[PDB]
Length: 430
Ligand SMILES: Cc1nc(N)c2ncn(C3CN(C(=O)c4cc(CN5CCN(C6CCCCCC6)CC5)n(C)n4)C3)c2n1
Ligand SMILES: [Zn+2]
Ligand SMILES: [Zn+2]
Ligand SMILES: [Zn+2]
Image: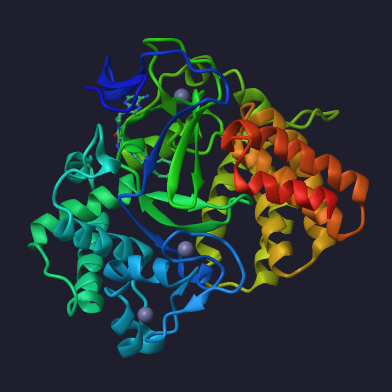
């Protein structure tokens, strides 16, 4: 199945539908772009980005009716109106209690899009939204109850402005959205919004992917990070590649109900380094290691929950205490330590403790470089944060160096002409 040039849809043995190359692609080549089928700017970025096109700039004009949507100009505002009108009056009516989840917000837009544009869109050249996997038969009752709550919230916040299909159809759709929806992030991997990119959702998973997905406004772009030969399958990663094999496959199993057999998962080459044990005089016993791994996974999950109701200083305390406890057995380059160091850095940034955030960054960066693959956005984002921190604290040489490391990754991932790169070059001069 063809039309996107140089590519086709096919049946990948052992995996199912996928995407393969018909022509070579070199590192940094653009395979395809996919316009968003539906998308929504996250609430905390309102006023910083245009709701229609996601341009980040000053001096955006306001929707006069609700005062909660911002735009480059009246053309962006008018083009956004079919989607924005789903929320404009409801925000006025509900005021401070207007609070649908972002999943609910995105699903409302999908429904409006289906009504206005029932035919195949340019976002769906090889895979249609209706063909999305739901995994509905594999979901437990807890997840199905959350789907029913989303349906309830959809009705509650959007009923004046949408006609709904039946409960059965919404259950399928919500399940499809839960597992197919993408996040759009900025250059520091900060959350900007959510979107549906149907053609991107065709790609199968590898823990050594040969492409990387980036965003230019609401457009997804897919570039090669390894050489791809004619006839080879195009693989993205569905999950965070920092973690060792068991953890990667736990996340794959819980969200998509499969496990990976790629070369990384097969060989487990990076696993030993990822869970590095301190080389002490009396080395830690095997039991103690299992104990500390168990503790680490617990605190990682505990911390995920705790950030919905603890203060910044309490969160930093959990990070510090967990790091102290883990350091009896784990090296600082160990991925569970890096996890908590990364959370700590974010808490520091939130509190405007620039020095503290910088110190955490300096310890994270070299382990990141080794644990992630070559052209990782996680690595690039960390160099950029370091660079910006260094610049702000007047370490101009160190800052320039870090920003250059960011650029060298981003030229490949984002393309040399991406506006993010122009902005970062300006920071090196200014
Ligand atoms: C045996 C085997 N081995 C493999 N190596 C492999 N690779 C892919 N598969 C099959 C099984 N698949 C799915 O269950 C699937 C695929 C998608 C599309 N999703 C992916 C996540 N996508 C982002 C990931 C990035 C971060 C944001 C979240 C969603 C959205 C689109 N869904 C919702 N289910 C396809 C494989 N099977
Ligand atoms: Zn705009
Ligand atoms: Zn409005
Ligand atoms: Zn794998």
